[PDB]
Image (tube, rainbow over all chains, first blue to last red; front, side, top):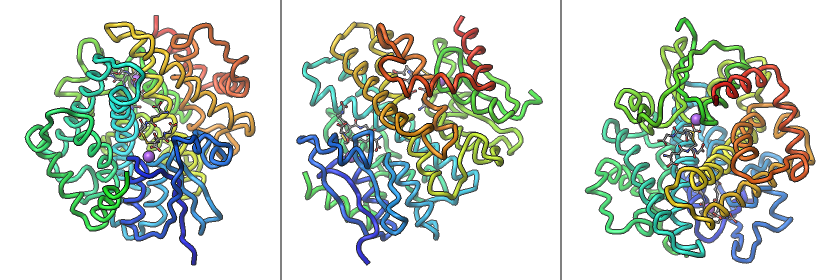
Length: 218
Length: 219
Ligand SMILES: N[C@@H](CCC(=O)N[C@@H](CSSC[C@H](NC(=O)CC[C@H](N)C(=O)O)C(=O)NCC(=O)O)C(=O)NCC(=O)O)C(=O)O
Ligand SMILES: N[C@@H](CCC(=O)N[C@@H](CSSC[C@H](NC(=O)CC[C@H](N)C(=O)O)C(=O)NCC(=O)O)C(=O)NCC(=O)O)C(=O)O
Ligand code: NA
Ligand code: NA
């Protein structure tokens, strides 16, 4: 055949692994292309032709005339809508539930990722240490966890009464938050429903497999 | 009331007016409820039942058994998918281009909004003034405009060879960036394709109507 997809990514980043989880859960074949962000490969003309935003990940579907799509959650939606026909990890397009799923994916993409990412930036990469900025995004991480907790303490999954890509989407950034960004953090005590949700998801065979890969990387 | 939708929103923020544009473009009736964020109305138990994130906007469709959805771009997708059957401002669900439309909407939601929003925060609300932080997000604003420019200099619209909600979605934050977040900004000079794109969208009857409502609301 040749592998169906090419996934432009890098050794270890939260959004690439997120897409990898979707691919593995769907049993889809893919070849990862690891861009060296340190060397600016993602800002080179060759990659800009794939994603003009110059960020990873991006996906090419070789079975669909090399249809190319970027933004990890748009990539995710493309994958489940077209290739999760048995609805193993997604709700059906054309239903009200689909937009609740979409709502949660937008909360992840606009409410979790960018804000956690600023915590990561100010703690690690910003040229000067700014305690008030570090504080600001640490507080936002806890707020976001509280939003998850308020729903997960009331129902088992975010949508569809089954684990979906909506639930999956929060995993990689929450891992970074718990294991790097937050200090003296006790996930299970502070956000019990969310911690338990997180634990179960990581126990899914496909997710656990990728999580082991992630550990082996970076 | 009597109106098909209730739109939870407020006077100043860009995402509510963005949804208002979609509703007006589709000719749908709605009653806006303007919440006072400085009175913590969005963090009250009553609104948290509507959106547990405690942010605006949120939409209730009274014609669809009060189906409720939040996240402005998720609300937008719901509206065009269900109510834009003639595809006046959107591409068709089930196509490939739908996911390109979605891609651009995620770029707006995750690449424009939150970063422009951090420029807003550090420039206006953060209780200490931090030049390196202000500079960081002003820079990112310019980078984002550059991304738009690189595409719009080569094609008329983001997707489907017609104006869609993907194009519309960038308007309100770009307005704030152009007039408030950047200093001595010259849209047409710095980003000519994007500025022309911006200008054309603002000429649309429905958008011009909302833009005036927004202008009066500021004031
Ligand atoms: N919305 C996009 C986010 C993708 C993304 O951020 N990719 C990162 C690698 S993950 S590393 C996490 C990443 N931070 C960065 O990329 C830091 C560098 C950046 N230029 C900056 O100045 O902030 C971040 O905060 N992301 C927010 C999020 O995930 O929502 C990247 O390509 N960086 C190259 C670059 O920007 O030059 C998606 O979901 O696909
Ligand atoms: N992704 C959401 C964003 C919705 C949103 O941010 N609504 C704002 C009003 S617009 S005002 C713009 C807003 N800034 C804020 O909300 C500032 C207060 C905030 N808690 C903080 O600390 O940054 C922002 O940066 N948004 C990023 C974006 O639009 O993507 C709100 O309800 N704030 C109440 C609150 O947070 O308490 C959407 O598109 O619906
Ligand atoms: Na990534
Ligand atoms: Na708003």
